[PDB]
Image (cartoon, rainbow, N blue to C red; front, side, top):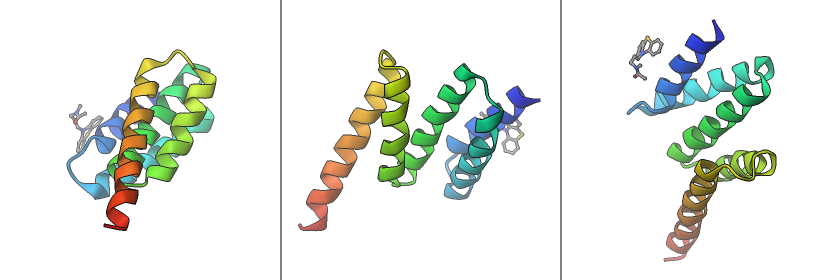
Length: 97
Ligand SMILES: *CC(=O)N(C)CCCN1c2ccccc2Sc2ccccc21
């Protein structure tokens, strides 16, 4: 079912290993067209999470900015954007340090 596939992908994105994170991202992109309104919004949040944990901050930011245009009152999405911003800001500083 779709709920079990999501839970599997969710756990992959929270895994301690980067192979799993990348797999979970792939599975999440597969689930996305088959999803209801609410499901897709969930998938997108964890796609931004997974990309953030992989240091793919520009992709993470792309997803979270869309989520915020769809659900502007989503405080969890606001927090994740804040974190992505902080990470990219510091990465830029370190690049020329
Ligand atoms: C989120 C999490 O880690 N849970 C719920 C424990 C079960 C983890 N797995 C899992 C991990 C590694 C290999 C196989 C499986 S089977 C499976 C199926 C659906 C959801 C999670 C998990």
